[PDB]
Amino acid sequence: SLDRICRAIDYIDATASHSRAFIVEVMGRHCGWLGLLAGLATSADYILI
Amino acid sequence: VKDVLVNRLGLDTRVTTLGHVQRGGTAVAFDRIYATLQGVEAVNAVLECD
Amino acid sequence: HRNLTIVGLVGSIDNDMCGTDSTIGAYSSLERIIELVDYIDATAASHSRAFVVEVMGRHCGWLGLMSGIATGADYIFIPERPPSESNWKDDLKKVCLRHREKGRRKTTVIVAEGAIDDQLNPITSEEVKDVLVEIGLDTRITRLGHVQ
């Protein structure tokens, strides 16, 4: 699951540009492990876990 | 979250939602190796049980 | 520098530009959609499940169409041939349940960025999800976004 998330973030990072923000809506109802680890692996700016 | 980025900051925000993508596909090497060994252990545990 | 020498290359995921059979980026973008829908499809089928894929491409239904063929989608939403505002929901239901009757357990709908009804009203993937949910299917939206 963590791999699927990072595969998407990697594709998002693989581009150019000012005034751009990107939201990755992650599946995982009870824990924040996926959010935290994806955030760590892809050096995300802000995580909502 | 989108409105904060679009209205409080001047950012054009594009949302990406994985959905079922996050449950589909083949298991990664770690999941295959570990799920397999766990299956083996689950059997032994069940047999060794008293 | 009296006579401008200007040449144009079509760098577009859309595939909207006229005169060219395909634009630079179109097939690659299509591959990204396929990449994702392939994961959705790569699970052992469940009894009452549905999936909605919100695909990008603002001005042309090419990505929506090609994804439809490439993934064996039940229904697709394209700006070139939009459904009636009056009965698109009822036609969606018909098509899906017809396939479900024939054995299909992996109901997939593809919604283009520019998806509309014949009265120019946009069709959100959330709108589509709600239709399939009232048919008794556990529906899941997948928005490709900037991945494409």
Image (cartoon, coloured by chain):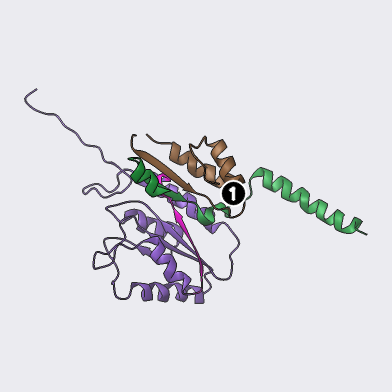
From the top left corner, tell me how far across and down residue C110 is, in percent. Answer: 40, 60
Q: In which quarter of the image is residue B9?
A: top left
Q: Is residue B27 left or right of residue C96?
A: right
In this rendering, the answer to whether C47 lies above or below B19 is below
- Chain label for disc 1: A
Chain painted in green in the figure: B
Q: In which quarter of the image is residue C83?
A: bottom left
Q: Residue furthest right?
A: B50
Instruction: Identify the amino acid type marked 1.
Output: Ser
Q: Which residue is drawn at 86% across and 54% down?
A: B45
Task: Say whether residue C75 is visible.
Answer: no
Number of on-image labels? 1
Q: Residue furthest left?
A: C2
Locate the N terminus of chain C and report the quarter of the image it occupies: top left
In this rendering, the answer to whether A29 lies above or below C118 is above
Crowd band around label 1 with a 10 angstrom C-alpha radius: few (<14), some (14–19), many (20+): many
Chain painted in purple in the figure: C
From the top left corner, tell me how far across and down residue C15 is, in percent. Answer: 29, 49
From the top left corner, tell me how far across and down residue C79 is, in percent. Answer: 28, 60
Chain painted in brown in the figure: A
Q: Is residue C26 left or right of residue B22?
A: left
Task: Say whether residue C67 is visible.
Answer: yes
Q: Is residue C9 inside the magenta stretch?
A: no
Q: Name the residue under label 1.
A: A1
Q: Is residue C144 inside the magenta stretch?
A: yes
Q: Residue at x 42, y 74 (%)?
A: C93
Start-end of magenta stretch: C136-147
From the top left corner, tell me how far across and down residue C135 is, in percent. Answer: 47, 75
Q: Residue furthest top?
A: C1
Q: In this view, does C82 lie to the left or right of B26?
A: left
